Amino acid sequence: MVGGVV
Amino acid sequence: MVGGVV
Amino acid sequence: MVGGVV
Amino acid sequence: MVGGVV
Amino acid sequence: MVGGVV
Amino acid sequence: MVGGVV
Amino acid sequence: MVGGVV
Amino acid sequence: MVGGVV
């Protein structure tokens, strides 16, 4: 489970 | 960039 | 949002 | 197994 | 096993 | 926020 | 950059 | 379990 913002 | 993996 | 069940 | 991304 | 990211 | 149970 | 891993 | 902001 991975979530991100760049 | 926005993203998610379950 | 990211969610999971196993 | 149940999962989601929103 | 249950998990989340918000 | 990040949370999990195992 | 913002991110989380469960 | 890891969460961060840069």
Image (tube, coloured by chain):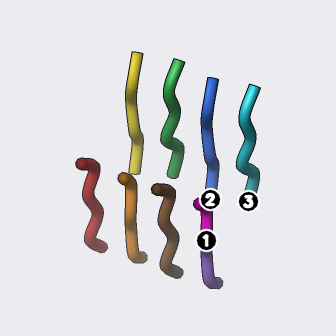
Chain colours: A green, B yellow, C orange, D red, E brown, F purple, G blue, H cyan
Chain letter for mark 2, please.
G
Q: Residue at x 24, y 48 (%)?
A: D6
Q: Is the Cβ of the residue at disc 1 closer than 8 Å to that at disc 3?
A: yes
Look at the image and tell me in which quarter the C terminus of chain C lies.
Answer: bottom left
Looking at the rendered structure, the secondary structure element under dot 2 is loop
Q: D2 or G3, which lies in front?
A: G3
Which residue is labeled 2 in the image?
A: G6
Chain letter for mark 1, please.
F
Q: Which span is picked out in magenta?
A: F1-3
Q: B3 or D1, which lies in front?
A: B3
Against G1, residue D4 (above or below) is below
Against F3, residue C1 (above or below) is above
The amino acid beneath tag 3 is Met
Q: Residue at x 51, y 52 (%)?
A: A1
Q: Is the Cβ of the residue at disc 3 closer than 8 Å to that at disc 2?
A: yes
The amino acid beneath tag 1 is Gly
Between the residue at mark 1 and the residue at mark 2, the CA separation in whole angstroms equals 7 Å
Which residue is labeled 1 in the image?
A: F3
The amino acid beneath tag 2 is Val
Against C3, residue D6 (above or below) is above
Q: Would you call the spot at circle 2 few (<14 residues within 10 Å), some (14-19), or many (20 or more)?
A: many
Q: Are marks 3 and 2 on the same chain?
A: no
Q: Residue at x 61, y 62 (%)?
A: F2
- The total number of labels drawn is 3
Which residue is labeled 3 in the image?
A: H1
Picture coordinates of residue B3, whole percent (x, y): 39, 30
Horizontally, is E6 left or right of D5 in the view? right
Against G4, residue G1 (above or below) is above
